[PDB]
Each structure stands twice: as C-alpha cells, then as structure tokens.
Image: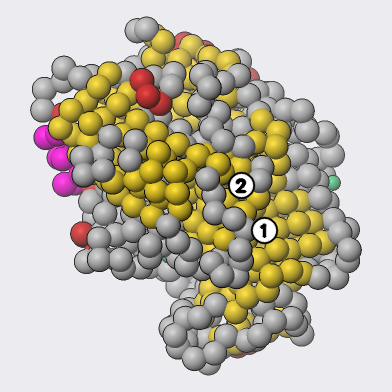
C-alpha cells in the first residue's frame, strides 16, 4: 500500500489569492444548509495567510480549518458562522460540522457559532466575542469548545447546556441548564444550581486532537502530546509538545477502499487519513498497531454492512481516532465500535488510546440497527467529545425500525469521558462497569418513542437510567450531568431516574439534573430513588447537587 497522495475533490483548499473564495464557500453552503441526511461531505481548508471580507457559513457535513502549525497563522478578517435561518431560528438540529485551527476578527465584533451536537470548535482564536445562540434566542442544544481562546465574552444565551475545556475566555455570559468547564481560564465560579455552573480547575488528562497542516509546501499531521491536569490552551505560549507526521506516512483513504486494504495499510505501518466521503465496509477496520492515527476530514463516515462491527482497536497504546461518523447499516450490528478486546487488562496510562469527535448515528438516513454502539474495553481510554445518537427524526426511525439498545458501555478501568452526549437508546444510554471512571459533562435525552410503560420496564425499575454505574463498582466520579425526557408517543410514561449508581463512599456525583421537555413524560427522581420528580409542562429541571 502506498502512502501519501492527493486529498481528492471533497477537500477544497484555499489560499489568500484564490479567486472568489466567498462565492465558492457560499455554493457549498447553498447545497449543505438544510442537507441534514445527505451523503455529500466537504472539508474546507485554508492555507496560512490573512483572508479579508469573508463570511464562511457552515452547513451540514462541512468542516473548516486552517493549515498553520498555530491558529493565528490562518486569520479571517471575517467570520465562521453557524445560524439557524433554515429552521426558523431553532438551532437544535445544527449537527455534524466543525471548525478548527483559525483566528477570527469577526466583522461586527461577535462571531456566531449557534450549534447543537457534533459541532466541535477546537484550537480557535476568536479576537472578539463568541455568540453561541441563534438570532432571536430560540432553542439550541450544544456544545463543545476545546483548546480555544476567546478574547471577549462567550454568550450562550439560549443554549441549554455546554462543555468547555482547556481554554481561555474573557468572560462568560450565562448558564441555562448545565454549563460545565474544566481547565478554563476565565470560567465563572462553581455555583450550581444557580447559575448552573459546574467548574473544575483542571482536566485530569487531555490530549489535543491531531490535525492536518502545511509545513512549508508539505502536508503533515500534527500529533499533540498529552497533558495531565490541563488548564488553558496548549498553543498560547507557542508550539506545544507533539510530533509531526508527513502525509506520505498516511494511507489516504478514498472511495473504493475496502476494509481489507485499510487493514493491510495499518499492518504495514501506515496511519489513516479518511478524506470526506461515505465508506461502506464488509468487515471491521482493525487498528492493532500502537500509536496509529486514524483521522477523518469533512465528517468522513463509515457504514458497516451485513451487521459487522465498523471499527475495532486492539489492545495497544496510543491509538488516536478522530473526526469520524459511524452510521449503522440496516442489518443489526452487535457492536459498532470496540476499543480493545473483551477482557482487555493491559495498562495504557502513559500513552492512552483516545476517541475524539467520534460520532455514532443509528437510523435517520435510512433504517439502522445496532445493539451496543461503543464498547470501551481498554483501560485508560480517553473519550473526548462523542455524540452517540439513536435517531429521533428522519427516515428509518421507529421503536423497532431503528432499535438501538445500548449507547456506550465502559468496561475498562481509569477511563475518562470529557464531553459525553448520548441520546435515545431503547435501554441504558450509558453503562459503566470499569473502576475509577470519570465523566466531565454528560448530556442525554431518553428515547421519545417507547410505546408504553412496559416497553421500558427494567426489572423492578420503571425505565433504564441514562447513566448507570454498575452496583459492583467501588470508585467512580461524574460532574455536570443531565438527562431529559420527551415521551411524545405516550406522555403518561414515567421514568424512575436519570442516573443509577451504588451507594458507596467512592462513588460520587456532582451537579445532576433531569428535565421533562414540555410535560411529555416525567421523572420520578433524579438518581436512584433520590430527588424530586419533574412536574408540569414548563420544562423546569429537578436537580441534585451532591450524591451520595
Ligand atoms: Mg436534540
Ligand atoms: Mg478490567
């Protein structure tokens, strides 16, 4: 297998002398603005330089990034904008897009990034304010900022929840249901429940997402080294610790690539660069070599056919999976993504495997089925930004039609999730069986389409927790976690709790909430049989500050 080669027609590369950049980006946006489930994919890439009079509007399945080693190398006098015009001001479906490695001088002083899930904002320098809300302050369900510097105020306004890590902000305007911060210089003080700020001084461990850049005229991928007890940006005081890999050390995956070829590339020592597109596989992609980077551009998507697993990472150190959507096929897959083997017991603390900006979809673009979406077997794994989503709208949706029982199952020890979003599973959205797990920020919605109370009976419990720590676990800790319900098929359904965990000194939670959306169903409790039920139709959270 040969490494390197052209990035293909879905990677649009601009430099400051490119004619009609605005017209080019506008045409991508015209096509992608409302294209929620289409198969088209785009990566917009900007060579280092200064770009004037630019407003890059970002639609579905569109990534935008600069190609400098540092964010300020690629500067827009202008904006990278997501708004909600196509949905009449409602931003709750602004999914599957990304911005990375750019500096912005927004034209009116404020850049708008009004997104919901799977819309990461990484390694950005906003020289102004950042507005996360749609014009008109309608509903929005974000969001994720990492390794970024916002010189002025971040204004969430109507954003329901948000996670920011390892960043610097000049100010922070408000909280709604759950704004969580770890390692954020300028974060508002811990104040939950009012305002609902969950604030941690540092992030226990983080490792910034690898990214494509240009070293002179040569393409390379920069691979940041890990930080322990991280705080502030990695690039603020100049280039961080990390390694650069030349593009010729990557198999550049395009249409036509089989799992057999991809697997052969990894076995031969090549890393993986998935150009934007949709890749069907008839057997799992297997990454069994330590330190392999598997990096996707433009929301590159993998669909497993015939019920196979899409991606299996072996029991090795340092695998970095980033920027991929795994989209279930119509034939049920027992698992979509497995990190490590069943029973994996190896230590990877010094050099963990990570999933970053890995998104899963079951249904919505056609019928899709999977029993468990992500199984994390390997000890020390970092899950840093994931959205694992059983579709509630689109094509191929139904209680059976797109049944997906379990979202994420964590079996490894010392696993860390930062920015965990899991929604709509028929049974437990997240289950955690390994020891010493930590979650910083969780957002869940319960399945809308349970037909009746019996359909979600869980032994002698009504409903399955959105986040379940197994009763055998001795040590676990979670911060800033919310579960919301919208039982619209049968609003008489009651969900016993959002969270379930054993009662032990080393199993702790901080800042939990449950919310009924418009009275469609209600929660009886917050965690276990503790905390007040939700009531009425006005969407007021029920909260618990500390457990146990
Ligand atoms: Mg939503
Ligand atoms: Mg174990």
Is the Cβ of the residue at disc 2 closer than 8 Å to that at disc 1? yes
Q: Is residue 106 above or below residue 469?
A: above
In the depicted structure, whether residue 286 falls above or below residue 448: above
Please, is residue 468 above or below residue 2 in the view? below
* Residue 145 x/y as whole percent: 48, 45
Q: Is residue 345 left or right of residue 136?
A: right
Q: Nearer the viewer, residue 39 or 51?
A: 51
In what element is the residue under mark 2?
strand
| Residue 125 against residue 8 in the figure, above or below | below
188 sits left or right of 417 in the view = left
Q: Which residue is mark 1?
A: 479
Q: Is residue 19 magenta?
A: no
Residue 81 falls in image quadrant: top left
The residue tagged 2 is 182
Disc on the earlier residue, 2 or 1: 2
Residue 28 included in the magenta stretch of the image: yes
Along the line of sight, the residue nearer the viewer: 238 or 7: 238
Q: Is there any visible trace of residue 113 in the rendered image?
A: no
């Amino acid at each position: 297998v040969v490494g390197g080669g052209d990035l293909g027609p879905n990677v649009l590369v601009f430099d400051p002398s490119t004619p009609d950049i605005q017209g080019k980006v506008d045409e991508v946006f015209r096509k992608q603005e409302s294209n929620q489930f289409g198969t088209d994919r785009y990566a917009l890439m900007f060579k280092p330089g200064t770009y004037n009079d630019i407003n890059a509007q970002i639609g579905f399945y569109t990534s935008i990034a600069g190609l400098g080693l540092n964010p300020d190398d690629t500067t827009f006098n202008g904006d990278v904008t997501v708004d909600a015009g196509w949905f009449d001001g409602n931003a709750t479906q602004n999914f599957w897009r990304s911005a990375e490695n750019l500096a912005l001088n927004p034209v009116n002083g404020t850049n708008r990034w009004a997104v919901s899930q799977a819309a990461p904002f990484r390694r950005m320098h906003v020289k102004g304010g950042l507005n996360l809300a749609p014009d008109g302050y309608g509903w929005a369900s974000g969001g994720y900022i990492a390794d970024s510097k916002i010189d002025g105020e971040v204004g969430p306004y109507s954003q329901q929840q948000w996670y920011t890590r390892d960043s610097s902000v000049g100010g922070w305007g408000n909280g709604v249901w759950n704004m969580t911060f770890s390692g954020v210089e300028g974060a508002p003080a811990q104040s939950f429940p009012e305002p609902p700020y969950t604030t941690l001084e540092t992030t226990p461990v983080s490792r910034e997402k690898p990214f494509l850049y240009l070293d002179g005229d040569d393409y390379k991928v920069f691979v940041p080294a890990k930080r322990t007890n991280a705080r502030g940006t990695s690039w603020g005081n100049g280039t961080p610790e990390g390694e650069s890999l030349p593009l010729d050390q990557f198999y550049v995956v395009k249409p036509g690539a089989t799992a057999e070829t991809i697997n052969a590339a990894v076995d031969q020592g090549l890393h993986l660069l998935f150009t934007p597109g949709v890749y069907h596989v008839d057997q799992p992609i297997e990454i069994d070599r330590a330190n392999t980077v598997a990096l996707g551009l433009g929301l590159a998507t993998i669909i497993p056919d015939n019920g196979v697993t899409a991606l299996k990472v072996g029991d090795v150190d340092g695998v970095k999976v980033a920027g991929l959507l795994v989209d279930a096929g119509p034939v049920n897959s027992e698992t979509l993504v497995e990190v490590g083997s069943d029973g994996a017991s190896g230590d990877h603390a010094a050099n963990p495997t990570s999933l970053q900006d890995v998104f899963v979809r079951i249904g919505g673009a056609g019928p899709g089925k999977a029993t468990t979406s992500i199984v994390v077997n390997s000890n020390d794994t970092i899950i840093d930004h994931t959205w694992v989503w059983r579709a509630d709208h689109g094509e191929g949706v139904g209680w059976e039609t797109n049944r997906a029982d379990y979202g994420v199952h964590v079996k490894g020890d010392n696993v860390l999730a930062t920015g965990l979003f899991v929604e709509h599973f028929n049974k437990y959205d997240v289950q955690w069986s390994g020891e010493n797990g930590k979650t910083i920020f969780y957002q869940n919605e319960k399945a809308y389409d349970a037909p009746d109370q019996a359909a979600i009976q869980n032994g002698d419990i009504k409903g399955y927790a959105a986040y379940k720590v197994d009763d055998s676990v001795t040590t676990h800790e979670g911060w800033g976690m919310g579960s919301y319900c919208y039982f619209n098929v049968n609003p008489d359904i009651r969900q016993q709790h959002g969270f379930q965990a054993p009662v032990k000194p080393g199993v702790k939670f901080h800042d939990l909430l449950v919310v009924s959306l418009g009275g469609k169903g209600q929660y009886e409790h917050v965690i276990n049989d503790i905390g007040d039920p939700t009531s009425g139709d006005t969407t007021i959270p029920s909260q618990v500050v500390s457990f146990p």
